[PDB]
Image: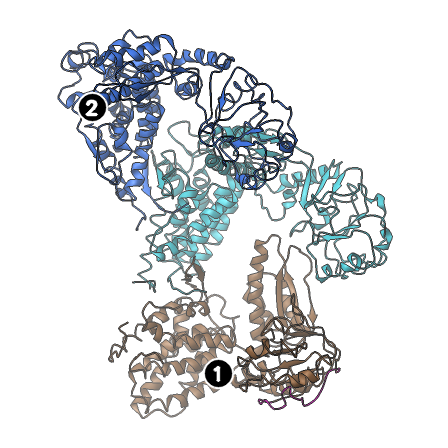
Chain colours: A cyan, B blue, C brown
Amino acid sequence: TEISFTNKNDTREIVDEVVENAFSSVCSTMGPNGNYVVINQLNSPKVTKDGVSVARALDFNEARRNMIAKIITEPSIKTDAEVGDGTTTTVFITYHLYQKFKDAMSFANTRYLDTLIKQVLQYIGTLIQPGEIESEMFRNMLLTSSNYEEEIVDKILDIYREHKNPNIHLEKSPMLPADEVKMTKEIYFEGSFPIETQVPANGAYVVGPEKVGVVLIDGSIRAYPTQLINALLNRFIDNPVVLMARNFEPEVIAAINNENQRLGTSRIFAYKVNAAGLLGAGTIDDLGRLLNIGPVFDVNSVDPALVKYNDVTLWLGRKGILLDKSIEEVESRADSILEGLDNRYEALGIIERQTPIGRELNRRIGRLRANNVTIKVTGVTVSDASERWARYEDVMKAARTGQQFGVIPGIGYGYLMASKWLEANVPQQSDEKLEKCRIGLIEVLRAQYEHLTGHDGSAENPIFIDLVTGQESDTPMNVYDNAAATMIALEGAWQTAKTLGKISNVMGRSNTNYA
Amino acid sequence: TEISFTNKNDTREIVDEVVENAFSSVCSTMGPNGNYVVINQLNSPKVTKDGVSVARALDFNEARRNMIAKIITEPSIKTDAEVGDGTTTTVFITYHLYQKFKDAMSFANTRYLDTLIKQVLQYIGTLIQPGEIESEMFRNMLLTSSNYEEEIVDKILDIYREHKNPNIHLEKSPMLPADEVKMTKEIYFEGSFPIETQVPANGAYVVGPEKVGVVLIDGSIRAYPTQLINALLNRFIDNPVVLMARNFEPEVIAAINNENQRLGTSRIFAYKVNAAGLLGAGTIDDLGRLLNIGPVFDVNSVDPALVKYNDVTLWLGRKGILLDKSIEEVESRADSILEGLDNRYEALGIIERQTPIGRELNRRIGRLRANNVTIKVTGVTVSDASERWARYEDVMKAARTGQQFGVIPGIGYGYLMASKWLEANVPQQSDEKLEKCRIGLIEVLRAQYEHLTGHDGSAENPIFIDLVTGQESDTPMNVYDNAAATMIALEGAWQTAKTLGKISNVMGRSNTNYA
Amino acid sequence: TEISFTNKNDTREIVDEVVENAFSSVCSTMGPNGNYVVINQLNSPKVTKDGVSVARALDFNEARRNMIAKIITEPSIKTDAEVGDGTTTTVFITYHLYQKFKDAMSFANTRYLDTLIKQVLQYIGTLIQPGEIESEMFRNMLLTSSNYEEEIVDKILDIYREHKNPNIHLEKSPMLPADEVKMTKEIYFEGSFPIETQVPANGAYVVGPEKVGVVLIDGSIRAYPTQLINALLNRFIDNPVVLMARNFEPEVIAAINNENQRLGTSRIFAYKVNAAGLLGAGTIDDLGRLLNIGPVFDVNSVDPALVKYNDVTLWLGRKGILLDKSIEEVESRADSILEGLDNRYEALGIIERQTPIGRELNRRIGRLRANNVTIKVTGVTVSDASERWARYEDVMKAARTGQQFGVIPGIGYGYLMASKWLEANVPQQSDEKLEKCRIGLIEVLRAQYEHLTGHDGSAENPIFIDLVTGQESDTPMNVYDNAAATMIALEGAWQTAKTLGKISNVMGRSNTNYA
C-alpha cells in the first residue's frame, strides 16, 4: 500500500489525469467569464481569479500525482517570476501541445517541433508592435490589473508618467497613509566588503574623505596582489587607496595582511564590480575618468600591484563618491547620460525582436542614467498590505515589460496571425508524414484564441484568421479591438511550455529513492 | 484527510448541497410561523430562532462543506455586525438569486444585472420612511410588544425625548421601584495594559490624572522605538509619561518590558488605541489639545521619546480620564462633539439614501457623543423581570436602528414596490434572451414576500393589490397593515446577496494547501 | 512480514516481474528517443535520463522484489562506479540473456557458453580504436555537444595536449574572460582527525611542517595500539610525532583521548590513509623516504612507539605538507613518482587491450602523479553559466574515456561485429542441440542493435552490410557515422551481465532470516 513503480500504461493514465485537472482548473479562470477557484487555506478559504495561486495549490494527496504536478506547475510559476502573468497561457498551451502522446521520437517530429517553433517565434518577433507609451500603458492597465485595485494603477501610471525608468524600489508599508513615490540622486551597483577593514566606514559604510585616491581595475589582476610595495607606497600614509576588481578574489584575501598587519597605514580595498557580462570595459568607464572616479582600466591583468604610475589624493571628482554595501555616486555629470543615449539607441535597435542577450547594459542604464524611485504603499491592514503588495510588485513587472520589451497586440491575435505563418512559411507535405501531421498540429496554436473568445461566443477558428483578427483584435461582441496582453508572456511562456510539451509526454515512470 | 480535487460537478454538488440546505435552514425561521433551530453546544442544546445564531452554526463536519459554507455566511454575520439584522434575508435571497446558477454564461447579463440591481436599490432608496421622531415609532414600540409595559415602551422614548442618540444599557436588580436612568458622561474608546507595571492602578486600572505629560503616536508604531527611555528619564517624576500607540504594537515590547520596566521606571504608558479611522485620530484629539493629551500627531511613528516636541503636562482641563480595559472619560466640557460631530450631522444628509460610505463612518463618528443611559430592570417576579429584560433588549435595538438607519415599510412592500417598478420596468426592456430570462427572474424579487406569506399563503403577481399591497402596507392576514422592518436590512442584504449569487456559480473547484 | 519459502514458480514469477520491469525501466532511456524517468525523492521530483540514477532508485514496495532487484542493479552500479557509463548495457543485456532462463539445466550448455563469450570478448577487444591524439577525439568532442562551443572542444583537448591525465576541475564565476588554466602540483589522499586534539590546527586543519617525525604502523592494525607513549615521550618536543595507518584503526581512540591527549601530550597524529591499495603504501613511501614521512611498513604492530625503527624528522624536501579533512601536499620536486609510478607507466603496455584487472589496478596505482587543473566556466548570465557547466561536465567525461579506457565504435557496431564473428562462428557447428540452440540465441545478441535502432530500423542478420555497416560505422538513418561508445561499457558490462544472466536463472528459491 505504498510508493512503487508505475509502468507504463499505469503512468500514461496517471499523467493523462494531472494534465486534465490542471488544464480544466486554469482554463477555468481564462477570459471575461472568470470562473473562480476556492483555494483552501489554514484559515478561511481564499477565493481567486488568480492563475498563479491556482498553480501553487494544485495539491493532491497520492504522492505519485503530486510528484507529477510539481513538474507542470514549475514553468507556470517560472513565468510568474519573470513577468507575473502568462501562467494560464503556459499551463494552457502545454496541454494543447500534449497531443504529442505518441509522437515522442526525435528526428522528424522534433526537428519540425524545433525548427517550426523557431520559425513561428521569428515571425512573432516580427509581429511585435512597440508597446511603450502611456496611452499604450493605458491599454495595458485595462487588463493587467485583473480589475482589483486601480489605486495601484494610478501609482504605476505616476511612475512611468514621470521620469524615464528610474530605480523602482521595493518597500512595503502596512501602515495606513503615504503612498510614497520619491526620487533621490543615487547610482547604486555592487561593491562591498571582503573584510571590514577594506571599507572606509564600518557602521554605515560612508566614505571618510571626499576626493580620495581610488584606483580602478575591472578584470582579474592575477599578479597575486600582495605586491603592494610601491603601488601602495604612492599613497602610503595618505588616504584609503580604494582598488576595485571583478569577483576575482583569490587567496590574496589572506595576503591583505601585507598592509593590514604588515607595513602600510592606508586603508586598501579590493572587491567586485558588476556580475557576469561582456560589459566590463563600460562598467568601469562609467565609473572612472569619464566621470572622474578612477582610471578607465582595460580588461587585463596589466599594471601589476608592484607599482602604479602614481596615485594622488585628488584622483576622484567633485561629486558624491562613496564605497558602500554597493557603491554610491551622486551628481553624475555627463557620461551616465552618454551611455544612456548609447544603450537608448541600442534599445531602439533590437527591441523589435528584443533579444536580451547582447543588450543588457540596460540593466544598469536606468540605475545609472536615471537615479531612483523610492516607494511605499497604503496598507490598511497587514494582510491586505501583503496582498496589494504582491499585486503592487506584480504590476510594476508589467510596467517593466512595457518599458524594456514592448506590448504585442492581442492575446490570441499573436496566434491567429502566427497561424497564418503556417501557410505563409512552408506548409508543404515535407519528407515525412509525421512532419505534415506536425504542421497540421502547430496549426493548433489557434486554440488559445478559440477557447478564449469562444467561452462567450464564438470559437470560430478557421474564419477569424485572415481578416477578422486584425489588428489588436481578439474580437468580442463589443468593439473588435483595443485589447492586448503583453509580449514576453506570449512568447517566452510559449517557449517554456514547449519544454513541458516535450517533457511531460516523454516521461514514462515514477520511482523512489532518497538521494 | 483526503482534501483534494473536486472536479467539477462535485463542486456543483458541493455547493448545491450547501446553498440549498442552508436555504432550508433559515427560510422557515422567518415570518410568523418560526420553526426553530436547535443549535447544539458542546454541552446541552440551545434552542433558537433567528438566522444570526443559526448562521454562526451552519457547521458540516466535512472540510469541503465547511469551506463552502464559509462564504455564504461571512456576509450573514457581517450584515448584523453592521446593523443587527438582515442575516436571514441575506442568506435566503442568496438562494433565490442562485437560480442564476443555470445561467453560468453570465458576462452579457452581469453588466446588465449588476447595474439593474443598482437601479433597484435606487428605487428602494426612493421608497423611504425616515422614521426618527416618535410618531410612527410609537406604532413601532406599540407593535413590538403589544404594549407590554408602558415603562418598557415609553421609557426609551423618554430617553430619546431629551438626550440625543445615547448608548443604551440595561441591568437587573431584584427590586420594585423605578428604573435607574443614568445620564453620565462617559465615551467608550479602547486602551488597556501591556504589563501591569504600566498602569498606576491594578483593580479597576483607573489612571489618576495630574500633570499628565503625553507623547502621541497616533499612527501604527512601526519605526520600532527601543529608544523610548531618554525623554522618560528627562521626564521621570515631572509627569506621568503617556505614550499613545496603535493596536498594532510590534515586538519592541519585548525590548521594553526589559528596559522601561527596569531603571528608568517612571509611570510609563504605551498601549493601544481604537481601530483605523478618523476618530482613530479624533478620540486622541478632542481630548487632545482641548483636554490634555496633545496636538495632532500624524498617522506615523516618527520622533520617539529621545525628547518630546513640547513638554505638555499641565493642560488638565474640565475633564476626567480613567484608563480601564478600555480607557474612557468622565464629564468632559470642551467642544469634543462641536469639533466634528456637526460635520457628521450634516453628513446625516445622506440618511435619505444612507449610502454604505457612511453607514460605518457616521455610526463610528457621531455616536460617541455624550451621556449613555444605563438602567436596571425591575419586575415583581424573576420570570416577568426576565421577560421585560429580553423585550427591552429587543426594543432598544429597533429604537437604535430607527434613530440610525430609518424604518421602512418592510415585509415585501420594499420588494414589491420594486417588482412593480420593474414591471413598468427600468425602461430598457430586455431584447437579449439572457437578459429577458434574467428580468423574468428579477421578477423573483417577489419571492421573499411570496415565501413569507406562503408559510400560510398567498402571493401571486396579479394578487399584488389584494394581498401584497392590500391594505397598502405590510399585510399580515389579520389587519393588513402596521408592520415595519429596518431599511438597512433590505438594502445591504440585497447587495451582498448579489455578491453571493455572483460567486457560488462562478465558483468551479476546490483545492487544498496551507498557503 | 510473510516472506518465507516461496515455491518455486513463485520465485520464477518474482524474477519474471523484476527483469521485465527493470528492463522497461532503462530500455526506455536509450537511444535517440530518450524517454525520461522521474526519480522521486521523498521530496520533490527529479527528472533524469541516465541509468545510473534510475538503477539507483529501482525500489519496489515489497521486500521480495527489492531483495531480488538488489542483484540485478548492483553490478549496474559497479559497472559505472569503475568508469561512469555502461549501466544500461549491463541491465539491458542481462534481460536479453535471460532467454537462457529456460536452460536452467545448464551444465551441458553453460560450459559451452563461457567458451563462446570468452571468444566474443576476445573479438570485441580485438577491434578497438583507442583515440589518444585529437584526430577523431576532435570528432568525439565535436559530436558530444553538437559543436556547441569550439572553445569547449578546443580547451579540454588543449589541457589534454600537454599534461598527462590531469584532474579536470571546473567552477562558476561572474566573470567572462579567458579561463583559468592551473597545472598545479598537489597530491590528493585522505587524512583527518580521530579526535580534534590530534590536529595542530582547527580552522583548515593545516599542519605546521617542521622536523616532521613520522612513525608508521601502516597496515590494518587490530593489535589496539595503546602502547604508543614511550617513544612518544622519547620524541615529545623532538618532532611532531605522526602515526599513520590503514583505514583499519581499532577503537583505541578511548586509549588516545585519555592517554596521548593526556600525559604524554606531544603533537600526536594517528589516522588513516586511503583504501586497500599498493599506493596506500606508496604515497606514504615516495613522500616518505624521499619527502619525510618514513619507510614502508607492512601490516604488523612491530616497533610501535615504545621505540621506532628510525627517527626521521628533518628529511623535509621540496614540498609542502598540509593536513586537512584529507591531507595533501603541494609542489613536490623530488622524483617520487619516478620511484614507483613509472613502473606502472611502463606496465601501461596493457593499454592496447587494457584488461579490466588493470583497469582498476594501473589507474588506481599511477594516477596520483602530478598537476590537477582547476578552471572556471563562464556565461553571460548565471543560467547559461550553469548550462555550459553541465555541458562542460559532459565533455570532460567523454574526453576522459577517450584518453583512459580506449574507444570503440559504438551504437550497434560492436555487437554486430560480434554476431558476424558468431555466424562465421567458433567453427564448431554445435552438434549438441542444447548448444545449437545456444548459439542460435547468442546470435540473437543482435538484439541490442535491434532494440536501439529498430525504433527506426533495421536489424536482420543477413542485412549486416546494407544498414548495420552502411555506411561502415555507427549507422542510424541520419548521417551513418560519427559516434563512439566507450570501450568499458560494451566490454565490462557484457561480462557482468553474462554473470547476472547465469545467476537469476539458476535461482530457485528465496528465503529470509536475520543473519
Regarding mark 2 in the picture, which secondary structure is present there? helix
Q: Is residue B262 left or right of residue A151?
A: right
Picture coordinates of residue C507, whole percent (x, y)? 31, 82
Question: Quick check: can you spot residue A269?
Answer: yes
- Residue matched to label 1: C124
Judge by depth and name the residue closer to the eye, B359 or B368: B368
Task: Give the CA separation, mark 2 to mark 1.
Answer: 108 Å
Residue B339 in the image: above or below residue B387: above
| Residue C88 located within the stretch drawn in magenta | no
Residue stretch in magenta? C298-314
- Kind of residue indicated by mark 1: Ile
Is label 2 or label 1 in front?
Answer: 2
Residue C439 in the image: above or below residue C63: below
Numbered tag placed on residue A97 in the rendering = none
Picture coordinates of residue B363, whole percent (x, y)? 41, 19
| Residue C304 located within the stretch drawn in magenta | yes
Judge by depth and name the residue closer to the eye, C403 or C216: C216
Q: Main secondary structure of the magenta part?
A: loop
Within-10-Å neighbours for mark 1: few <14, some 14–19, many 20+: some
The number of callouts visible is 2
Picture coordinates of residue B138, whole percent (x, y)? 26, 9
Residue drawn at x 81%, y 42% as measured from the top left: A211
- Residue matched to label 2: B383
Residue C176 in the image: above or below residue C472: above
Q: Are marks 2 and 1 in contact (CB under 8 Å)?
A: no
Question: Which of the 4 quarters of the picture holds residue B149?
Answer: top left
- Kind of residue indicated by mark 2: Ser
Within-10-Å neighbours for mark 2: few <14, some 14–19, many 20+: few
Q: Write down the chain letter for disc 1.
A: C
Judge by depth and name the residue closer to the eye, C48 or A513: A513
View extreme (top): residue:
B135
